[PDB]
Length: 551
Ligand SMILES: *[C@@H]1O[C@H](CO)[C@@H](O)[C@H](O)[C@H]1NC(C)=O
Ligand SMILES: CCCCCCCCCCCC
Ligand SMILES: CCCCCCCCCCCC
Ligand SMILES: CCCCCCCCCCCC
Ligand SMILES: CCCCCCCC
Ligand SMILES: CCCCCCCC
Ligand SMILES: CCCCCCCC
Ligand SMILES: CCCCCC
Ligand SMILES: [Cl-]
Ligand code: NA
Ligand code: NA
Image 1 (tube, rainbow, N blue to C red):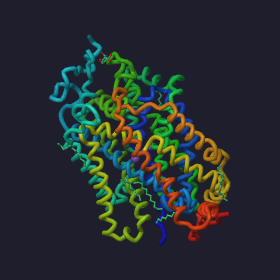
Image 2: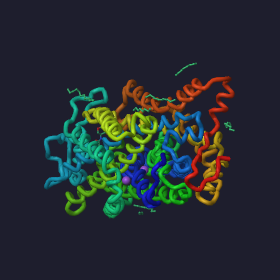
Image 3: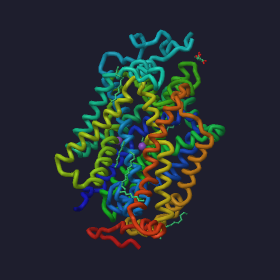
Image 4: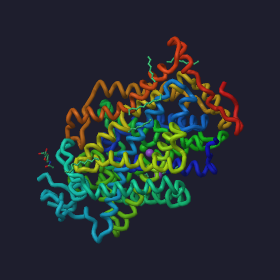
């Protein structure tokens, strides 16, 4: 009957902050900056952060607060047509839940490797190391040598195969680790949904307090001055390639968990007369500051490795995912008692990723339960659903656990819940809000909800800045198209790129397909059909709290 509200604003802030501040900050941003050269990644990043990151994030939160519904029915309130956006988000988040947890699996594996006398990536004299491996300290002291940390990441953790078309034998240890993290998610969602809520004082303060330590270790490294420069001074030429702009925009959208329905649901649990604008601005500041400062530390470590190895910074580690699994495990080796600090670091990674996964999976489950309110949300009948959603997404994730699973992970990362699909969904959200619902019409709601009409920046972002940025990046990437590559050496087969585009299209096609379906359901001439489907169905149809009216 009545949606359960937050106990207080503190609960909302802590839940959301633990929600969108996770592995998209300490893991994705590092190698996304590293892959796109150096500081040339920052110029689009911040622009999107001030052009589409904060505005769309606050728009999602404010729609959730205005309609008090999840990611799906909120659109039906705002606009019956273009409802597929919600479905699109669901598909996106589903695919995200498939490969996001895989990262945690790796972290868990690393954790299980930490509990021993000497870290396995300190020196390379083990069975999995190629004879070309040479220790980092001895690399520049005196061809094509490899470092123990990278060896451990590829040969042992991943057992990397020649290509995607050679999946090979499934790795059982990583499969068990993925099962373990999915079991943690399952027992933290069906029961103990607020388990992290009562221990936030450890779940929120520790991940930051740990990062600072790395930062203190990062800057002190002798080569940091080089690395920070690589992280800061941009390259003008790199800005010409569409890849940097697409990566920066989609990294903004991924870090803030927008176009997923999680933000709308989180904003659906708060009060109507709640000043979510200021809270959202502070949370976005915290998110971007965490990303920027963590990049400082990891790029200082990269500069240290480059100066010690006698190699260029751009060729010191893996450009694809695993930079955070190459730089940070090397940094924790330099600290006194490396085992303890490595354990703490991977525990912090687990906390961040697990909290983010809890939020995303719970949002997806709530959305699907909204789609099936009688067939679900009936106790045990709901419980089984959880056991379904994890399992079908666990088995589907097992394709990323085979020793050729890294390439599949790269496909999912670049296409499934990131790339031109996120731009598609964000552009359609902003188009519906600005050019159909009306920016001033939604300011009429904001002014009543928070008590003051915000500045013209929010409306200018949805009206012009965000659609223009999204369409420009999309069309400019399609014009100067470069095939997706893993670690800038592997050239994907055509069928692999076809599968990745199928993954993107699974969510993209929801917007037009649902439009066609809704037009088919309604009767009459086309013009009155679209006019009737473009009328909001009383978005703030609530009287329990002090509210005004739609016009
Ligand atoms: C490593 O080998 C590759 C492939 O032959 C070559 O392109 C590259 O220059 C070599 N790098 C070093 C550091 O020897
Ligand atoms: C010879 C080992 C089995 C064949 C290759 C592994 C395939 C695992 C895919 C799991 C998907 C559920
Ligand atoms: C700029 C492209 C959109 C043109 C305006 C469409 C608005 C239709 C809905 C009107 C609601 C009264
Ligand atoms: C009108 C309500 C039903 C819309 C269903 C859309 C589902 C899209 C699935 C995309 C392929 C998995
Ligand atoms: C990965 C498939 C997601 C299916 C979502 C269905 C929404 C009605
Ligand atoms: C490492 C955390 C940095 C946070 C900066 C912004 C604080 C509101
Ligand atoms: C339930 C789908 C009905 C489709 C009817 C199509 C009429 C053009
Ligand atoms: C030049 C070092 C800056 C570090 C900011 C946290
Ligand atoms: Cl970020
Ligand atoms: Na978190
Ligand atoms: Na983030």
